[PDB]
Image 1 (cartoon, helix red, strand yellow):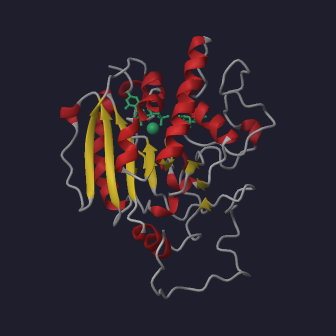
Image 2: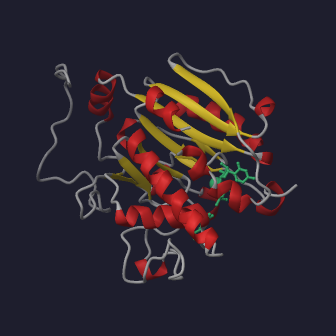
Length: 291
Ligand SMILES: O=c1ccn([C@@H]2O[C@H](COP(=O)(O)OP(=O)(O)O)[C@@H](O)[C@H]2O)c(=O)[nH]1
Ligand SMILES: OC[C@H]1O[C@@H](O)[C@H](O)[C@@H](O)[C@H]1O
Ligand SMILES: [Mn+2]
């Protein structure tokens, strides 16, 4: 049950003026695409606070990636779901290396120890299995948000993202035609998408939804990866390839614009991006991913 919103004073939405004319703001299956200028965060904060919404945020910090936790968590504290209840779950092979970050009221952090895998491909892939900690999330949070660690929040990332199932547009492909998307293209892979299918290229690094829908997604991607292994094939972009196939066949109820995961070093700051909210931290691939 959802009590009445209190009286609020805000700009009237006008039917005969779009919030943004430069970008697509709803998908052909009527899911909002979340850009700056599309949402009144005051209205959304009300609706979500009245529900006493708790958001879990998952983050893997295995081997050398523990170094990214301090900036990731301190900037989450400045910009992620502020004012709402938040439960961070830090999955790591080095519990003692998790930095001591001071949290705002109503926010908590759990350290979950997991095995490290040698191959960075396997570390990335096995997130899906490790997420799908099954009874725990169900009892502790309403939504789960699953992101990469080698990132920092620079601007607001709040309840406008929450919905049963969301993906995020990959910042390198939001302008491309589908034939150029780097979907898995070999029909022997569970992740296979033919050249005339596909809505968008979503990122492995930022997806989420209700606990129920995230567990479905992560369970399905984990089972598909297990079939490919048995068949001696490994998807071209690993977990991200399977996530793309899943979201093709199970349409997300919201899509986040590339404001929600950007790399300014590689792509600059285009006019179409009014805010850069959560962004890649520079890293040396070869050195950070190997002993
Ligand atoms: O040695 C590793 C490699 C990967 N990761 C986790 O897997 C994620 C995805 O890998 P990465 O960020 O290296 O992929 P990229 O964004 O460069 O494609 C990282 O954000 C970490 O959360 C990790 O913890 N340790
Ligand atoms: O083509 C897909 C790839 O694009 C790169 O820009 C990215 O760093 C990879 O992790 C993967 O998403
Ligand atoms: Mn990353």
